[PDB]
Length: 114
Length: 114
Length: 114
Image (cartoon, rainbow over all chains, first blue to last red; front, side):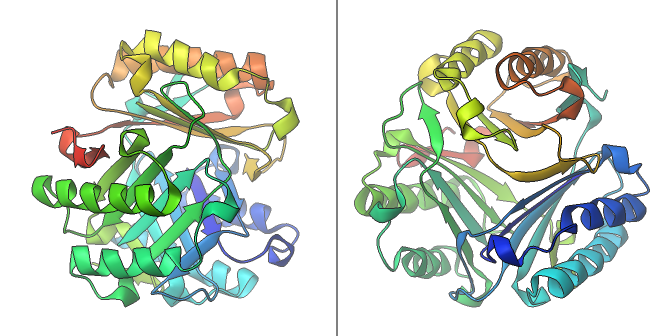
């Protein structure tokens, strides 16, 4: 699984260790080993949510499986929770796009997961 | 809806008010309230289009519905028009990927839109 | 086609001409004309892969067709090869998401490819 956060929060406001905390919690939520979790945080972005520039985030979570209506609700609670507690972004200024990737459509280590 | 522009145009060339303009014009084009529209502009990127580093943009529009053949033609006319007029990017150096997102696959405010 | 590379490798480590090399090799691999190939390289990112901040990359390749099990295996070999050789990123620290885009869902030059 791979989780990307794009935010207008500045770099200095991303706490030390936040990528590990994401890695860990994403591992627990998806059931996948942490070795397979990738995280990418993009601060200082020029962005707007609902027409204003208070803290916000545009995110994506891609996974081979473990994506669905109940699981995504749970992920959104977890990830909005973390964004609120660590980056101080209100949950109502966060979008998270979920993508259930086919194994044949993810490349890694010179081939695909298929 | 969420609209992302990635471009090699420099930051100083993005006009003041461009994110509000995009918010307003996308609210109008999609019919959605502006409170639900998110916009993200990423200048100064290292990019090429047809191998050239002349001005270009790679964009995405993600929405729960309001995506389809005729709508997307209309969005492309709108958005290429805005990128040409405001950022001086030729329409033939713009790509916009459209995504019709399932409500169950968009997280927001601690849950999904489902 | 559009190929995006996000990496923690620093900008100074991206060799001169790397975007052209990608454009050329992608054209040959996908069979698509080079004029239609867009490339985007984002260095200096804040990321983790398996929890570690050792060199890594999160990538995407979008194309109208030419996406499939065998093709994607071939692309992954090619692109991991290039990331290893040019950016010194281990293939096992690279994820590439593949997207077969509907023509009606790609905007370009004021319209779509449909």
